[PDB]
Image 1 (cartoon, rainbow over the protein chains, first blue to last red):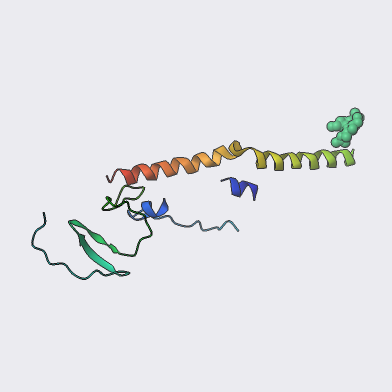
Image 2: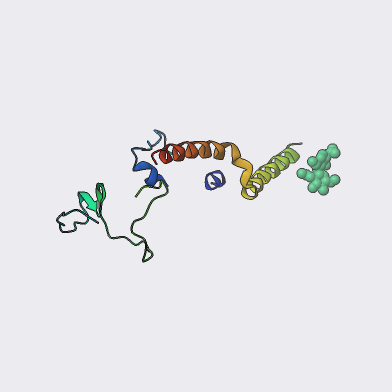
Length: 27
Length: 50
Length: 49
Ligand SMILES: *[C@@H]1O[C@H](CO)[C@@H](O[C@@H]2O[C@H](CO)[C@@H](O)[C@H](O)[C@H]2NC(C)=O)[C@H](O)[C@H]1NC(C)=O
């Protein structure tokens, strides 16, 4: 949890810039 | 100074082709919660796009 | 020395917990990857202007 807590998208996406989810989720 | 174009009714919450006083594009028009100052005519995103 | 070793280990783990809670820069190696990619996309998007 400490590691995860320590370490715009619309504006980018709207130009044909999508982000694909990882196959393996954090869980 | 604008040409002799007829205006249409404003349509919200639908995908439309729009032309606002010469500004053109395709998108969905929704009511905004942005506080435009009295002199501001349009806004831009982080990407500096309308 | 089993009791000492277990104590030294448990203490060392506690130190990691505190070091991570305190020092923001500890994960700079992962944050740097995130930052490089964020810059690459922002640069790409700004080129449209
Ligand atoms: C080896 O070093 C450890 C510390 O790393 C010694 O354990 C400490 O002993 C002092 C007394 O001098 C205690 O006040 C500390 O609380 C102890 N620390 C731990 C983690 O137990 C250990 O006694 C040393 N062993 C030898 C043979 O010198």
